[PDB]
Amino acid sequence: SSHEQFRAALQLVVDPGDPRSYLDNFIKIGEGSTGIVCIATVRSSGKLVAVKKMDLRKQQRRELLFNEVVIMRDYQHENVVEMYNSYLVGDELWVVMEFLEGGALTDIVTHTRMNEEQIAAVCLAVLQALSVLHAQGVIHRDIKSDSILLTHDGRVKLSDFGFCAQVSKEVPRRKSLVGTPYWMAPELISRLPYGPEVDIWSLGIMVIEMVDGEPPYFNEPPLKAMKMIRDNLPPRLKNLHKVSPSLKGFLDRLLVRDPAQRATAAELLKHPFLAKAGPPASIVPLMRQNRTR
Ligand SMILES: C[C@@H]1CN(C(=O)c2nc(Nc3cc(C4CC4)[nH]n3)c3cc(Cl)ccc3n2)CCN1
Image (cartoon, rainbow, N blue to C red; front, side):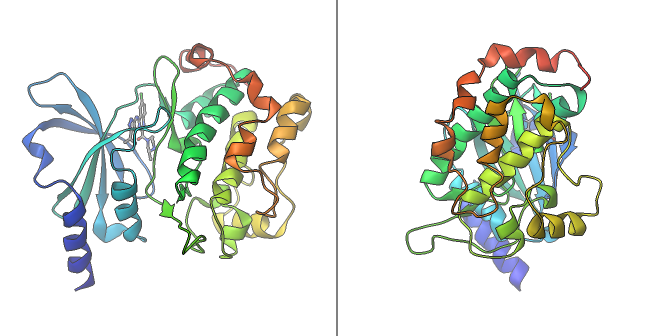
């Protein structure tokens, strides 16, 4: 049947065997839309790893977990969480990854104000990842603060590629409605042909997260937020008058409704706002203390 076909297919691109041959002491530390994140310990070693566990039977778009394992195989980039191995355990896909001990950007945003040196540092790190991914035809399609992980020394890496897509010379655009409603680009909510530009819109929403502490429409039912994103003017900062002209001029190039006028990752990397971008040390205080907005 279709599930057995897909499971056989997935078995062909993952590593063989059971990672319980070398992983001990699984503990759930978090969850996302497709499954849970555990920490585990390499047997006979002190090495800590993160393991994503996704039940195939619960997935709305199982083919995109194929994309994650395949496209991100041995992807080595300073701003991308490293994937080590993948396995099929019963009806679950397990993906063994680097453990980032600074936590997720979501936790920083909810507990503290960030200054613009810190906001620019985070944006620089994400756009360096996206600029390369987009040049290779990879659309992430789930950019948001929960997809951003930090090290204790303040490095910033992108993860959560479970919704990603590959575009090509032959098939340069997608139309699938995929992502997290409050961060979705309007042309994607509209199921119009779209390219990597949808990640740039989502980054704009994450910038609003970093400035305001939440995305626009965050307490609205998700279908209503999607209707307002699709139909209304781009959402604005609640704290509009507390940010510099540089940051607003930057944000104005991300939250552009027309994908053909929205800035690309490579263009944004040249923007004057990112000359503010602080070094890893500027991020470190954000994981150790809180400062209300
Ligand atoms: C849907 C997921 C849910 N998340 C967590 O559960 C998650 N991941 C972490 N560290 C990771 C994650 C990974 C890959 C991605 C396995 N490596 N290191 C965390 C580290 C600390 Cl200190 C505190 C809380 C954490 N929560 C954050 C990412 N988005």
